[PDB]
Amino acid sequence: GAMMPVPNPTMPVKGAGTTLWVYKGSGDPYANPLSDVDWSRLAKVKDLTPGELTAESYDDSYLDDEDADWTATGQGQKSAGDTSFTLAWMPGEQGQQALLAWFNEGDTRAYKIRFPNGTVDVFRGWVSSIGKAVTAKEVITRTVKVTNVGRPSMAE
Image (tube, rainbow, N blue to C red):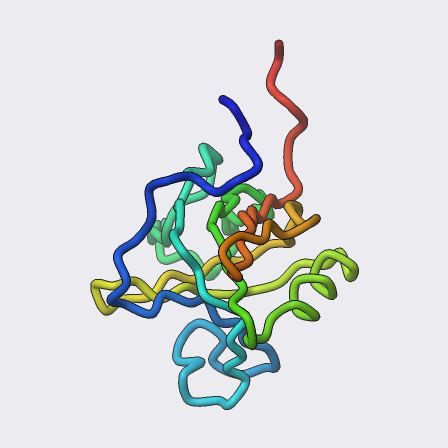
């Protein structure tokens, strides 16, 4: 593309407050984290791009046979499922130390972004896209993308 400095023209209409939140601790992590008070907002997310993983992972693939007793089970640690989302920092908001610490730490994290439909998407991994923030019209903007650790680059 062009990789221009300024942010793209297209943008979400001002109406819904889209923002991702991060939770930690223990106990019902994905089941119902809303209960615990680990809820910690990071910042406002302009948009979210739920990319694919193209991995060998899948939902519960249980299956009985001869009345087995967990003699054999399938489970892999395939790490694939990056998440590209745009961010924005307003004059008087919070999240700077969050991002800086995120990249500075270099560790995996579990966060989720709320959709305008009233639902929520849970995604994990470590942020790989963290550098400088673009300032325009007294408004800061920066595109963050979380890339997990898996296979190397494509084959030519």
